[PDB]
Structure formats: structure tokens, C-alpha cells
Image 1: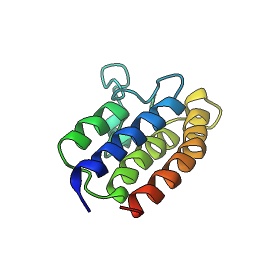
Image 2: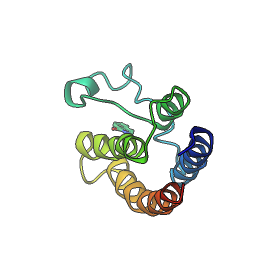
Image 3: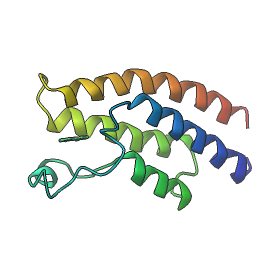
Image 4: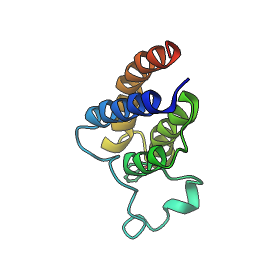
Length: 112
Ligand SMILES: O=c1[nH]ccc2ccccc12
């Protein structure tokens, strides 16, 4: 497999995932200044901006490593927030809508 088309695919996929996060609550790192206890519970914070940075730093050379960090966005949010919150529901919705985006993107990677 060639690097350039793969990274083009991942860029598109990340844009598509970001589109599902309509409130943009996962666009940037959880502000540790406003959520001071966040690192007490969450071992590896993740967000779409950080994913973009990782993508361009060649930290995603296969689909699984890409998907693993997306899954962290979801799981961190489910872990930190109570079930009766907007944030928790948003993570559930992102898991649902994102999974479909991921399945289609992976099929296109596998054709490479
Ligand atoms: O774990 C989180 N992900 C995205 C937003 C957020 C906001 C407050 C607390 C946790 C999170």
C-alpha cells in the first residue's frame, strides 16, 4: 500500500467523523483548566484536533491505530460523564454515527 492515498483517505474520514460531532464538543482537547480532575480519571485524552496532528505526524499508518484514537474520544467521554448528561449521550451518538463512517472508510483502505 502507498502512503499518500492512505493519508488522503484518513483525512477525509476524519473530516466525516468531525461532521457527526455537530456540537463540536470533541474538536479540541478537554480543557484541563476547566476540568481540573480530568487526568485523574482519563489516562489518554483524545480529540479530533490531536488526531489531525497525529495523522500528519504519520502516527496512523494503518486503519486500526486511527480507529483506536477515535474510540478513545468516545470511551473517555462515556467514562468521565454521568449517563444523564448531554456529553454522555453525545458520545453514544458519535459511536453510532462514527462506526458507519469507519466501516465504509476501512473498506476503501482494504481495496488499497
Ligand atoms: O471526556 C470528554 N470528552 C469531550 C468533552 C468533555 C467535556 C467534559 C468532560 C469530559 C469530556
